[PDB]
Image (tube, rainbow, N blue to C red; front, side):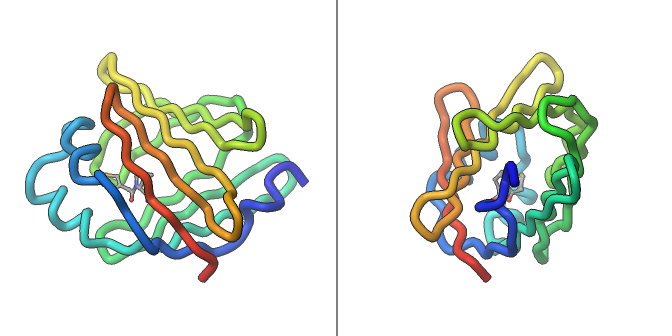
Length: 133
Ligand SMILES: O=C(O)[C@H]1[C@H]2C[C@H]2CN1C(=O)Cc1ccsc1
């Protein structure tokens, strides 16, 4: 029942500062422009201890499956090869990505009927709001 309130299909309804977040992470111009237009569907499911998070969009489809606290390999939508660990901290899913001596954290939170995604790289934060599809 660990992530019951996250489970479901969610659609992006608003974004703030995502272009700047992508710049901070290292994404190049053309990818930022195409990726920034996307309105992904985020689909979260749980089977036993395995959580799956899919992102589906016209830009790229991604899927990750993981156990909380157990590191895994991820290829991000912008083609970074990262080492990721996702934990639950006070009801927030905290996703840390490490690569090339850098780090970024993506937090996913249930707030009212929304799922709020906050992405941070050094001083740069982006907030992405999702609603039920
Ligand atoms: O899933 C989302 O809303 C946002 C936010 C969680 C981060 C990554 N993300 C994406 O969309 C995927 C992406 C696009 C270009 S680089 C990476």
